[PDB]
């Protein structure tokens, strides 16, 4: 039982309490809508700095919430769908489902290059009744670690990221076993990033309006392709 | 215009269809384990204001009730029993609106 357990419990709890809520409505601004994917954006300023909380929803046919979160968390397949990371490695293994990752992002010219140091944890939220669906969550939030101190090559960004997945199942035809034609993954994705620098907003917001849709479309499509023909992992 | 009775409800990916006690009242549907446990908290309810009631074309016993991404899957014992439930839910919804 590692030293971040209470911290992990608090982060997961906060996301499960406040991130699943459907759209502060008009406080959130829809910036991209493509099929079932909707990307919302908010422009907040607190403590002398302006930030841009990101929230997106998506419905993905033929995959379970368990499968989506597995592929989002598994560092071994990151290179197969992620396109902004330059390099990364596991700084520390805290448990079978919790690791500390250090990664550098490719420089979005002409802004300074960013690196990030975060704990990545995947956990199941058990269903309390037969009516409540099984929820899986991956939380990525920044932490400090002596092996990945601040450097003068990158700007250290602070993140609080969560992907929350729920599996909707429809009755199959007759008395048949469930197939992938009967499952739908409800994805809620939130990202609160502090860039840590002084890059102009127009560049930071245009880049976010461009990279978040591309990542969700590419990541979910990737999960669909890897699970095709495979037995369902609920 | 309220109604209650046993109906087969799709629950989760383990149990699938299970008999449950359904109650139409207060512009909503509520379901319980059985009639005996009505005075013991509802297991799930759905408001009918913006609900669509779609009968299944191939499963003549099945009718679905959806409010946005939230969906109930219900089976009566035969098409005759299904139509009575469908008509009751539409009449109750309309008289409540």
Image (cartoon, rainbow, N blue to C red):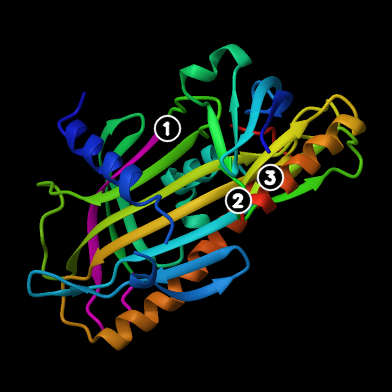
Residue B62 position within the rendered picture, expressed as x and y whole percent measured from the top left: 82, 35
**Front one among B71 and A37:** B71
User: Taking the image as drawn, is residue A110 in sight?
Assistant: no
How dense is the environment of label 3, judged by Cα within 10 Å: few (below 14), some, or many (20 and up)?
A: some
Relative to A40, residue A138 above or below: above
Of marks 3 and 1, the one in the foreground: 3
Q: Quadrant of the C terminus of chain A?
A: top right
> Tag 2's secondary structure?
loop
Q: Decide if residue A19 is on the left or right side of residue B27.
A: left
Decide whether the magenta segment is chiefly helix, strand or loop: strand
Rendered location of residue A99, percent (x, y): 29, 39
Q: How far apart are marks 2 and 1 (CA)?
A: 22 Å
Q: Which residue is drawn at 25% across and 74% down?
A: A113
Q: Which of B23 and A184 is in front in this view?
A: B23
Q: Within the image, what quadrant is residue A190 found in?
A: bottom left
Q: Residue B69 carries which label?
A: 2
SS for dot 1? strand
Q: In this view, does B82 lie above or below B57?
A: above
Which chain does the residue under circle 2 lie in?
B
Start-end of magenta stretch: A106-125
Q: Residue B92 carries which label?
A: 3
Residue placed under numbered mark 1 in the picture: A124
Q: Residue at the far top: name it.
A: B36
Task: Quote the CA–CA distance across marks 3 and 2.
Answer: 22 Å
Q: Quadrant of residue A98?
A: top left
Give yes or no for residue A170 being in the magenta stretch.
no
């Amino acid at each position: 039982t590692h030293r971040f357990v209470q911290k992990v419990e608090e982060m997961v709890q906060n996301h499960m309490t406040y991130s699943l809520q459907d759209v502060g409505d008009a406080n959130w601004q829809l910036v991209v809508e493509e099929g079932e994917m909707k990307v919302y954006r908010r422009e907040v300023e607190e403590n002398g700095i302006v930030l841009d909380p990101l929230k997106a929803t998506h419905a993905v046919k033929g995959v379970t919430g368990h499968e989506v979160c597995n592929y989002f968390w598994n560092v071994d397949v990151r290179n197969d769908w992620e396109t902004t990371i330059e390099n990364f490695h596991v700084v520390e293994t805290l448990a079978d489902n919790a690791i500390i990752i250090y990664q550098t992002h490719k420089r979005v010219w002409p802004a300074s290059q960013r690196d990030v140091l975060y704990l990545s944890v995947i956990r199941k939220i058990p269903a309390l009744t037969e009516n409540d669906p099984e929820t899986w969550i991956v939380c990525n939030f920044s932490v400090d670690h002596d092996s990945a101190p601040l450097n003068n090559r990158c700007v250290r960004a602070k993140i609080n990221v969560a992907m929350i997945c729920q599996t909707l199942v429809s009755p199959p035809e007759g008395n048949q076993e469930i197939s992938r034609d009967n499952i739908l993954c409800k994805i809620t994705y939130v990202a609160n990033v502090n860039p840590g620098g002084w890059a102009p907003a127009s560049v930071l917001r245009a880049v976010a309006k461009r990279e978040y849709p591309k990542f969700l479309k590419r990541f979910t499509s990737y999960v669909q392709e890897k699970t095709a023909g495979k037995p369902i992992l609920f | 215009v309220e109604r209650c009775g046993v109906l087969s409800k799709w629950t989760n990916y383990i149990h699938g269809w299970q008999d449950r006690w359904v109650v139409l009242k207060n512009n909503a549907l509520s379901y319980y384990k059985s009639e005996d446990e009505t005075e013991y908290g509802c297991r799930g309810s759905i408001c009918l204001s913006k609900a669509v009631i779609t009968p299944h074309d191939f499963d003549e016993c099945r009718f679905d009730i959806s409010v946005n991404d939230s969906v109930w899957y219900l089976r009566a014992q035969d098409p005759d029993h299904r139509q009575q439930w469908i008509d009751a839910i539409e009449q109750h919804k309309t008289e409540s609106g």
